[PDB]
Length: 367
Ligand SMILES: COc1cc(/C=C/C(=O)O)ccc1O
Image 1: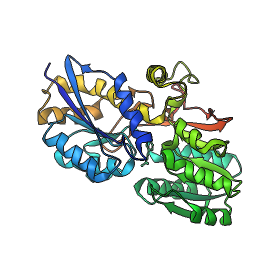
Image 2 (image 1 turned 135 degrees about the horizontal axis):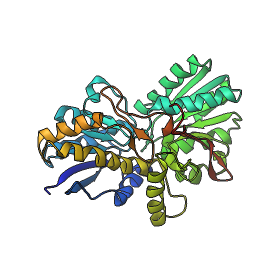
Image 3 (image 1 turned 180 degrees about the vertical axis):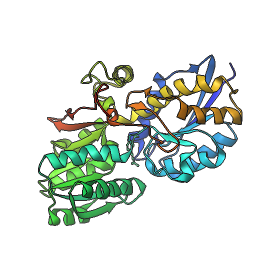
Image 4 (image 1 turned 90 degrees about the horizontal axis):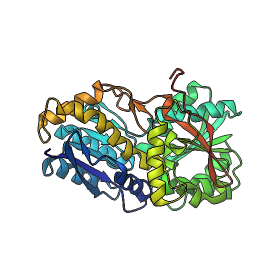
């Protein structure tokens, strides 16, 4: 019963607050002790800023002597947190997608779906609905590149033609010049590689300028905020999402159904109708991971030692089929996401509501 120390850096101020506030809110609904030991959870805002997240992670690993760290809410500070964790040798659970490199693989795993699983479900839909040419607009940063690179690699391997690439910066409040080019090229479909508030900006700008192709969005867009902001321009979007957005529609055999119901009932009872989100689920699921790996680490090591950090690291890879709201996690030395087809669905928006268009893979089918 000495504590297990968890440092979390998430984005609860600035425009990425749309992603970090739900992550931080969902901590009300996670375990407060594991295996006899209380969880000391220290939460700090980073504003989405890579330097502030580096500062928080640094102080967690050296001053707080954290056993685990988590964060951040968007890809650039998440990269920064991974770099701290892999230097300091501390288990890191990422709460936003990030490029895994050998520099980051040893000490980091990631809760959000990896870009290629999400891209696959979008591009298969494009192929099935008569799309040949695709344009892109996304952030001029590492998340923007993940998505563009996946669109080029997977999409071209499926016979899609990528006819236009545009970028914008996160704080931009206008994409007039990029929308101008995209409308000119008039692709059959446009993939928007963005998140939260910023994801609704190319959505509205494109419709206001009379684009009439299909618009596709990533799982960075999967909260009610996108509908609140995009209004009617949201209609008929196609959006990749984790299954936590619709546990009701899952088969009772889905290992993700129960925990998704658990999170959403609590979250929405507090925060209101349709307040569920892709993002709240990541911190909830991170604590489901901890519930599996910590009792295993506790057999051979005490909280607050390097040996405990090492034991968690190993357990992340020895413990298979970890059921959570967003998927069933089996991490490996080389797969730091640990996810398969059970971790994604496709949503549309119809009359201001998300509707599931394509279900996650069934438990008793191939993955
Ligand atoms: C918080 O959860 C998520 C965040 C993002 C945001 C990416 C970015 O803007 O860098 C994408 C997918 C997620 O599941």
